[PDB]
Length: 604
Ligand SMILES: Nc1nc2c(ncn2[C@@H]2O[C@H](COP(=O)(O)OP(=O)(O)O)[C@@H](O)[C@H]2O)c(=O)[nH]1
Ligand SMILES: [Mn+2]
Ligand SMILES: [Mn+2]
Ligand code: NA
Image 1 (cartoon, protein in one colour):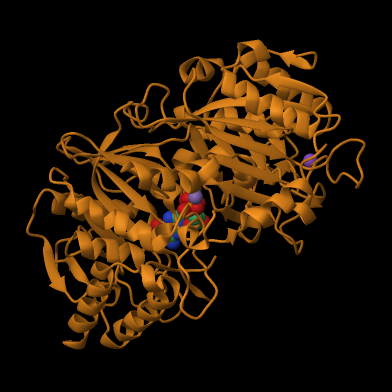
Image 2: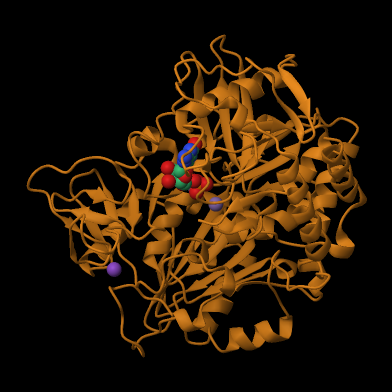
């Protein structure tokens, strides 16, 4: 109580009080700031970080900010990310011959050692911020509350954008369940190691842990993104996927968009692509086809549940976009360009001398006079060796500012999903687009997903490889079980490939807003249109079914080319992968789909 500098311990729901005070006794913060989520709290905290050189203000824009990190702490790190369960098998399938790549289990005993070696006294001299936050619209029956303790002001500010945060959240929680989220940069005062670029972090000791059985996320040593903004990956994919398994719903690495045709008919679609494969870009697409409209519900994470009527309802549980900045240009994503010019926090991009932002791929000239400070706080010119922005640099921006944010983006009941799309980067062999033969086939298609690393072609089932909160075999069984709900309206499932390249490494499909031509065919297919031709991998568009006018040289034969040699190779790789990685936990229906694809290919 003596150390509370905002709010009141007496005021917290009892269980929230125990969490705060228990971890205060452990971490030894100098003060405790219970966040209220107010504009005043936000602005004062921003100005404070500014005074201290933790952030700089971008004067070219309205209320925007730039943080530059320790180059040791620049990304979410999978090698340091663990899930603790009594049994390894509940976390990952026990692989047949190899090491698992579907999760990273740590015993409770090992974790307890790691914890006791990190957290005691870790917030000495620092403020513990208490962040009460809702993943999902505040009223929604699909929403879940978390409380994050952190000693990073950069985390509080970013969480205000990426979640719904504040007092109204505590008042909505009452004596209900919440996910316990503990974070420390791991740099108690006085500092024992030198502070780099005013960015507190402890790389040697970084550890991002999930303890689903205790409803706890415990993360240490990193101030960055997914390691520190605990609502996003840790809560909304890892903890949630398991919660969803227990509760009958789904927590997925999916964008949600609403699409409207020239008649005004509207549908919602969800899509799972791995990072750097274009979700944010699709979710706020500027469609090239006249009359068509795409509206954004979320760009990263979907929580979905069948309602009493059998509609699959999806909410975006985030309150903002945490997008990769480099590659973002008016040509590629004009709506992201529009959103990020106010109330936005940037991380590890270059700064122009007039107080604007810059990054590789921004594809927009600088005025004669304007110079560039790189993300490493050094002067920079287009012919230095280093990129001006870090490749994983970011904007953190309010969802409500996207000029095409969907009008139901915050509806507490969610939006009805009629189609689910899978995809990644495949330079060869995979057509632009196909549609699954059935639900069980579609689940197989999700399971089989592969994507060029950003020359290796990696497996990334459902775009969830880094995020499974529990056994992936069980997660497949959970997806298959959806067909066994009597009322369920199972959405059509599609697979796309924006990235097939021709013989000289050039893209066959222009992509971007031209992807609206692919969405149109999907939409028509959901309505039951006779626009599909059967192939060994599923339905592809008929000849002339796609609107290809205005395109120029589009080699359709090569684009939808299905080679026997490639697909024989593809099934072997899928076969081996599923055998090793899922092994005893592979559902029968999946093996059956694998057998069936092998057989259809063998008849070519
Ligand atoms: N060639 C091509 N590139 C794309 C397309 N969509 C997105 N990209 C690029 O893919 C990279 C990642 O895009 P992004 O929206 O950040 O993907 P996310 O990480 O999944 O949200 C960016 O450089 C984009 O310019 C597309 O349709 N075609
Ligand atoms: Mn994205
Ligand atoms: Mn993501
Ligand atoms: Na800094």
